[PDB]
Structures are given as structure tokens and as C-alpha cells.
Image 1 (cartoon, rainbow, N blue to C red):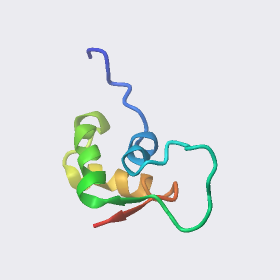
Image 2 (image 1 turned 45 degrees about the vertical axis):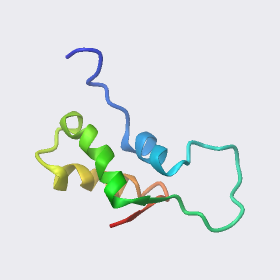
Image 3 (image 1 turned 180 degrees about the vertical axis):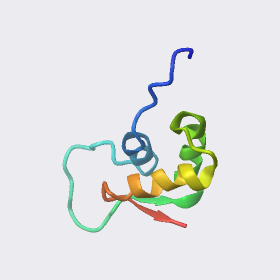
Image 4 (image 1 turned 90 degrees about the vertical axis):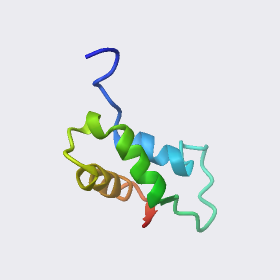
Length: 76
């Protein structure tokens, strides 16, 4: 289906928003990669038709469980 269909994982694109692309190793203190909700969901919208979800409730869902099991949070 064109040059796509193999969309990436929401753990590599979501963390992108916040800015945790493996900087190098600076776990000083605090800083838990916070991803606003108006942004995390936005990404789920771009892959909405690539995740096979019927609506955001189905997409943003994988973005909350996928953007949390890694350590990132979400500000509703």
C-alpha cells in the first residue's frame, strides 16, 4: 500500500515529542519525559489509519499505555 504500512512503534515516535531519543545518558534527577495530551494524541492521529483503530479512543489508548510503559507520562 504505497511506501508505508510498516508504521513504527508508538514507543519510538511518541518519545520523539517529549525529546527522549536516547540523548546519551544523563539521568541526573527529575525529568520523567512528560508528554502533554494535546500532543501525544496528535501523534496517534497521524498513525490512526496505520494502527487499525476505529477512533481516537482506540488510538490515543495505545499512546497512553505505550507512552507510559516506557517511563513517559501524559498531561491530559
